[PDB]
Image (tube, rainbow over all chains, first blue to last red; front, top):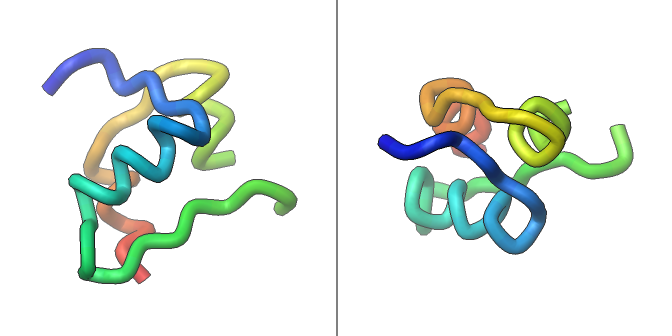
Length: 30
Length: 21
């Protein structure tokens, strides 16, 4: 894998490929 | 802080796939 740098646009883009339709939902407020 | 160590730093996909839910 590459440096795990994830920021919103990439955060979701990550869980999107890492999870996908599996159902991913990162946090934000908590 | 999944976004912290990940956005404000680096993290591991393992803990990232743990959010699959």
